[PDB]
Image (cartoon, coloured by chain):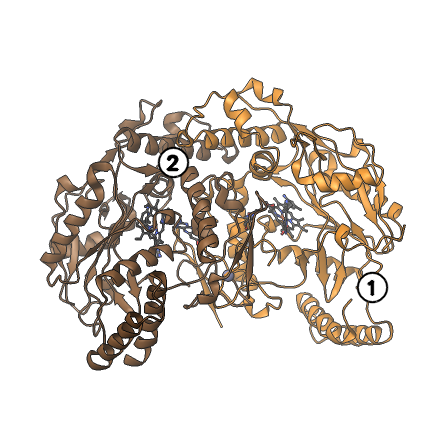
Chain colours: A orange, B brown
Amino acid sequence: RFLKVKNWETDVVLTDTLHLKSTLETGCTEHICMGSIMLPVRTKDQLFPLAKEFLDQYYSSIKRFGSKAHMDRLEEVNKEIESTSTYQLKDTELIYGAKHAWRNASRCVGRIQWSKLQVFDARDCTTAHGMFNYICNHVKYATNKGNLRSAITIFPQRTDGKHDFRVWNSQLIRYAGYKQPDGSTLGDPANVQFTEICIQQGWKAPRGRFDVLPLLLQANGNDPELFQIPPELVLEVPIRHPKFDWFKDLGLKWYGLPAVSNMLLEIGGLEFSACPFSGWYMGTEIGVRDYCDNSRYNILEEVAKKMDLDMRKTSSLWKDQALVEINIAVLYSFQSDKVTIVDHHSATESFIKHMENEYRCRGGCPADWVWIVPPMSGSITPVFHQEMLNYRLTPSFEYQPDPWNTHVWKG
Amino acid sequence: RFLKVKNWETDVVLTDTLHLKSTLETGCTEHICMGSIMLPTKDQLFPLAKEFLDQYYSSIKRFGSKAHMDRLEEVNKEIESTSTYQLKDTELIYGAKHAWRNASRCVGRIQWSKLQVFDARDCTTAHGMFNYICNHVKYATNKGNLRSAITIFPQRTDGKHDFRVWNSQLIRYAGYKQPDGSTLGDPANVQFTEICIQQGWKAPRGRFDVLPLLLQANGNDPELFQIPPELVLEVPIRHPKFDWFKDLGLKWYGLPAVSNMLLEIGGLEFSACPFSGWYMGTEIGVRDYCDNSRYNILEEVAKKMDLDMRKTSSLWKDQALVEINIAVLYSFQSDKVTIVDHHSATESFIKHMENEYRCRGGCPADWVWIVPPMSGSITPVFHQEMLNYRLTPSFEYQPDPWNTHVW
Ligand code: HEM
Ligand code: HEM
Ligand SMILES: Cc1cc(N)nc(CCCCCCCc2cc(C)cc(N)n2)c1
Ligand SMILES: Cc1cc(N)nc(CCCCCCCc2cc(C)cc(N)n2)c1
Ligand SMILES: C[C@H](O)[C@H](O)[C@H]1CNc2nc(N)[nH]c(=O)c2N1
Ligand SMILES: C[C@H](O)[C@H](O)[C@H]1CNc2nc(N)[nH]c(=O)c2N1
Ligand SMILES: [Zn+2]
């Protein structure tokens, strides 16, 4: 079977065969497309197939498919699963696995970078204090004084699902949000609930607009524990505008390191419930979403007032104008301080080259158009006009429920 | 099997039950999503008719009535005897309005019940088609106070006698390839212009030449007709602060009017059914002007603005884009030609969508098309989950007729 995708700007047509390896489901059927829906313990029985499929992939990639080493490794994992009910990945398999979960991440525009990923193996970790130390080292390595380096840290896999490692933070670095009695919000409205949990667990909140949240770390299924990331490890950029001198007085700043900590990494049927990973920002994640979503810092109106735009009618495009200026400011600021950042033109162009390369060398590149297209200026980026096919390959990153909904409190 | 959609900005959650009445296929499977692919006998006809007339009689609250049973029997006898049937005027009007209502890619559906339907089923020649189309254009244009309309030519019979408008829109600009190797005019219309030239059109060879209509009646060879120039309302494009903008020599036409789609009602196929509304600004300012494969003017505008075009990260493309879109809205407004901006249009669509969930149990919507091509996430549709599925009556794509027509 061959599926074809067209680029409507270039008329370039690509042929996908890779979708023949998809397994998980999309959410869609022949009768309903769920392409814009945000959220669409295993037995021995299901596990060996999942292991075998992964190991066949790994051994093929190293050009040892069907070798003695390959056969011995299948046998060894088979027996391990039979007597212990799970198995342990070799370091090389873990590295390959983590890289491939990124490569397979259909919502990620940054995948040209997938093969450069520093993998920190934290499977010897046993306590929350151990987790903290691992996470500080990740943050310090990844930050690299502004010259950002992609990295992932992987904590022990799930066993009975009663002993899970979890980072309760959605990202390693994020700002607190506090709902005020008057119904307004100080800081980041997205993190209000998590901030209440931190406070309830005994965090002493500074109660400012940009308070870096503490880490809340669960090891081996125990109750989570609080830790403050050392401030000197948290690189931040004050936001200023190249021509507008009043922009700095809005008091805005952001952190340099985007680091997702709430996802589940699946490799060969194993589940790594704590696997924080980080890269560097595309400017629109801060300038469009973090700053301009109505449910976030929501600064559009204030910016447009200061620019003296005509705000009496939407048709003056005042919002569009302020939006662009805010995004110029974010890129200017990061660049001026030498903190790695990529604009949405550069990132989507690199993504299309990556995608074409993948079709040629791998036979496809699953991609989720809804997420890949940037949240401003969509159609003047080359991804807008590119047809894409979304399907699920393993290894993969998956959503998991927030741990405060599922955690069995010990006390 | 009953589905929830959430808005991630407002936390409003709606339940879709309408999708259970969905009929055609999406292109998607449980293994692969094709959400971003642009194009993913008496026996068959009676169920299609019944399904339609049932929904019709339900809508006027006469479901199961004698008049309902009588029409069903009437239509059944007509199909068995004639191999087809004819819609009552009321059914035709209901069906055309519902095809718009069901158009999952249309942001402007709050307006769906205000559609003037022109019944041209009595039309027999290409000359007749031309007269009907001029009247549509004039009625819909209304000197700039635009009114939604559709004109419906006779339905398909044996498929050898199709009515077709060969143009993709009633009003579009010609495209010509130059000795230079560049393109003069609209690059999207190069092929269609060639056919027009080939059929005899005398091309002016300008940058904004309104194409002639190429009209096919009763499966005959199509004929050329020029729309009276005084019926084509055009708008010169200027900017409220940039004095130099008018010197780019840009204009666009006021009436967006799709002419290449097929309207299916109760199994009957209307292969020529031009329909028109009014523009959302970004259709002209982002797509028509700024697509690389269309008028592609970003670079010229950026240069006149004197932006740093050395690096993508100065966001010069984005700045010039916004300015071009301001100019479009400004020019249409100054000349009192109806236009809607993408903020106002998407806000209306969210209100429409809540009405439809409340009153109909859902609203099929294709997010990839609903979200405007600029400033996506500052419009409320970006944060709105949508379910895409196909309901009839419907507008459908059909093959370009020159690939199909036996000459
Ligand atoms: C190298 C720099 C990177 C850039 C510029 C980048 C870019 C992005 C962007 C813009 C998004 C969408 C975020 C949003 O709009 O909310 C995203 C999503 C994602 N990326 Fe990346 N990415 C990078 C590195 C990585 C790395 C290192 C990984 C994992 C190893 C990764 C895995 C993911 C995943 C799983 C998603 C989807 C998240 C979700 O569904 O919530 N990315 N990427
Ligand atoms: C009244 C003002 C209207 C507005 C503002 C509007 C808005 C739009 C927009 C922005 C698109 C996407 C266009 C593109 O990106 O190429 C669209 C698509 C569409 N609209 Fe509307 N619309 C209007 C009236 C109508 C009417 C009167 C009908 C039918 C009677 C209609 C049926 C459709 C269909 C079938 C599509 C998708 C066309 C395709 O798939 O090629 N619209 N609409
Ligand atoms: C409801 C919901 C579901 C979901 N899957 N994801 C979200 C939040 C989306 C935020 C993604 C975080 C940033 C992604 C990212 C990750 C990395 C590693 C680098 C970079 N530049 N950007 C919400
Ligand atoms: C290959 C292909 C398939 C397809 N379905 N559509 C296209 C392009 C779509 C052209 C859309 C025409 C304009 C839409 C429109 C129509 C109306 C009636 C009003 C308004 N404001 N805008 C290409
Ligand atoms: C409903 C819709 O799917 C949702 O708002 C999505 C749309 N596209 C997105 N795209 C990216 N990159 N990030 C997001 O958070 C979203 N949100
Ligand atoms: C590949 C992608 O589906 C295609 O370029 C679409 C994207 N969204 C669109 N949305 C609208 N309204 N109109 C279009 O022409 C397109 N093009
Ligand atoms: Zn789908």
Instruction: From the image, tell me which residue sits under label 2.
Output: B298
Q: Secondary structure at mark 2?
A: helix
The Cα atoms of the two marked residues, 2 and 1, are separated by 56 Å
Q: Mark 1 falls within which chain?
A: A
Q: Chain of mark 2?
A: B
Q: Residue at x 30, y 61 (%)?
A: B95
**Looking at the picture, how far across and down is residue A79, in whole percent?**
83, 76
Residue type at tag 1: Thr
Q: Which mark is residue A159?
A: 1
Q: Secondary structure at mark 1?
A: loop
Instruction: Give the quadrant of the C terminus of chain B.
Output: bottom left
On the picture, is A182 further left or further right than B206?
right
Question: Can residue A366 be seen in the rendering of this structure?
Answer: no
Q: Nearer the viewer, mark 2 or mark 1?
A: 1
Q: Nearer the viewer, residue A144 or A159?
A: A159
Q: Position of residue A319 (x, y in %)?
A: 48, 31
Q: Is mark 1 within 8 Å of ligand 1?
A: no
Left or right: residue B374 compared with residue A303: left
**Label 1 Cα crowd, 10 Å radius (few <14 / some 14-19 / many 20+):** some
Closer to the camera in the image, B22 or A187? B22
Q: Where residue A170 sits in the image (x, y, percent)? A: 71, 46
Label 2 close to label 1 by CB (< 8 Å) = no
Q: Is mark 2 within 8 Å of ligand 6?
A: no
Q: Amino acid at mark 2?
A: Leu
